[PDB]
Image: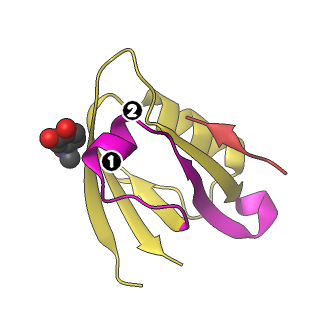
Chain colours: A yellow, B red
Amino acid sequence: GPIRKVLLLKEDHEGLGISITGGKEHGVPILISEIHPGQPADRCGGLHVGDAILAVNGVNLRDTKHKEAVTILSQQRGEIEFEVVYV
Amino acid sequence: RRETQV
Ligand SMILES: *c1cc(O)c(O)cc1N(C)N=O
């Protein structure tokens, strides 16, 4: 698919509201596997199960291990831009 | 399967 950039707005106490799979060690991109009702990804829309997360706020996640990606994603605050493509 | 909630 075409690359999209999608903004999420996250209150400081909440998570992004997604589950992810994949990563470098798995030979596949970081993939959104779940979108959690009522949480930022769900409320803002634009993200979907099956989207690959290529980058977040300018951090390239295309070659990061799963855990590295989790950590980077968990550190993001406030207004967060995802670069995604539907694979 | 590796899956993480964030
Ligand atoms: C997230 C959630 C929400 O209710 C609105 O109106 C807008 C967002 N976004 C996309 N913030 O950037």
Neighbour class for label 1 at 10 Å: few (<14), some, many (≥20)?
some
Q: Quadrant of the C terminus of chain A?
A: bottom right
- Indicate the chain on which mark 2 is placed: A
Range shown magenta: A23-50
Point out which mark residue A57 bears. 1
Farthest top residue in view: A13
Q: Quadrant of residue A12?
A: top left
* Whether marks 1 and 2 lie on the same chain: yes
Q: Say whether marks 1 and 2 touch (CB < 8 Å).
A: yes
Residue beneath the point at 33% across and 28% down:
A77
| Side of A42 where A15 appears, left or right | right
Amino acid at dot 2: Gln
In this view, the residue in front, A76 or A60, is: A76
Residue beneath the point at 79% across and 47% down:
B2
| Side of A79 where A52 appears, left or right | right
Please provide percent x and percent y for residue A84: 41, 66
Location of residue A67 with respect to A81 vertically, above or below: above
Farthest right residue in view: B1
Residue beneath label 2, please? A76
- Indicate the chain on which mark 1 is placed: A
Is A80 inside the magenta-drawn segment? no
Q: Marks 1/2: CA distance?
A: 8 Å
Please provide percent x and percent y for residue B4: 68, 39
Amino acid at dot 1: Asn
- The quarter of the picture showing ligand 1: top left
Please provide percent x and percent y for residue A43: 30, 41
Neighbour class for label 2 at 10 Å: few (<14), some, many (≥20)?
some
Is A47 inside the magenta-drawn segment? yes
